[PDB]
Image 1 (cartoon, rainbow over the protein chains, first blue to last red):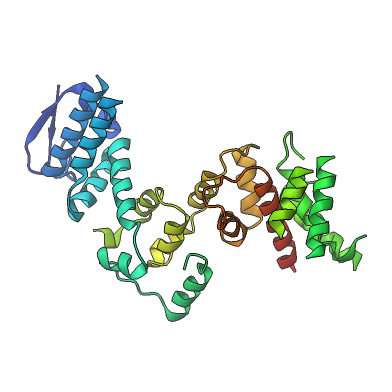
Image 2: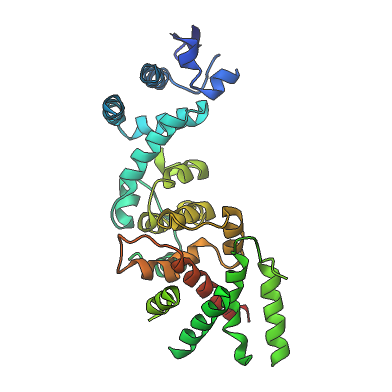
Length: 137
Length: 70
Length: 111
């Protein structure tokens, strides 16, 4: 039984064993960076993983993970930030797999367009990077 | 296509057990290096010594590697 | 905020792609390019489809990084070899061929 407060100031409570899934929290709680929504998402993830810890159940957990993964771009970015901050392997890995599936896409115009990435390659550098990876094209 | 064929076949024959341009011998260096238990002529010898210092050095398989070569 | 990701997040994302996707993303931008030239990602990609080699990862990584790196190991010789047998897994002779090719190339380009 531990109490976690977020930027919203809500003293979200969770069990000690469930909160132990975060290495940063276990080592050391204002938590000025993690937002209330993202903190609630990590709390739900930790609760579900603790329930699973205490196959058919394995694939049910994977399906629940896939359902929870369905969030927009900003939510996924914030989830990655929070997972990196709080030292959670599973959540960071799941978000990384989702982003990898997203970037498994088309020619570089697609990747630069979906992520609003603004490339500024010099013409020499752009052409050279195209030639040095010609095997893929 | 015969030079590389002879180089690789002789290299495999030696590993399982002339100095023109010293081109066959660099390929064997990785063979002795990544081994279980551990490992005009003057200029070629100097380059070979530099290569040896760089990487910390003081049959069906032969049929296969030739086959992938061509 | 994917447009302004740091190197660590880009590396973490790129840890779960294949050779085509990595060499593809290497042309997205400059920071993505720099993260894609990482040796660890290409070592993972090269060793993914080997699954039978063994001599110690330290020795292999040191020698391959000394003789050009794992990026040259892939595009020059590994990709042409895997082109007509995509499903086949590279065993022992493929490594003995590709590393010899890298040694010959390094000695030729030394001068």
